[PDB]
Image (cartoon, rainbow, N blue to C red; front, side, top):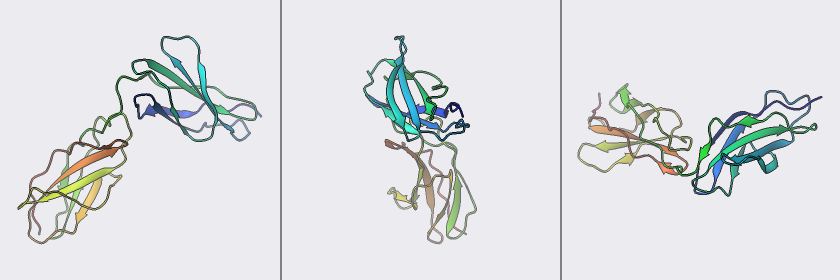
Length: 198
């Protein structure tokens, strides 16, 4: 038996004032022996030595503390075996601490179809910029004609599609969508026009 190959899908995000969040996927080959953990190392782009942040990580994610806002950090993860750590996986580009994580951008071109006397089927596109955190679903609001007071239609939805139901026969409705990531919900999207029943 031998050492594992390198971890996969090494990404970062959730950049705060003094931390960054690393996320990865297991290696393709364990070496013939089950893995024991992961090694997480950092190295500021203007410094020459990798320093070990943590060892024997069992999760597929790690939050690195104690980062100095306005530096740039490299990161690499390896996988642990009965034989010791395997080859390292690197982040794609340095982590820059000045730009914190925020709320996601508004979703894109909202569309509608399948209108009934009671329901409408709405689709939309994911936003371009998630704000530095992965998107955790979407929120759909509807606003009746005789009002400007929006009401959430159901619960968050991970898909970029939702069938709105519970609509009153013959009434006029416009719909808008917000995306959500870790630090909350986007400024709402480009609203639709008012649509009735059939």
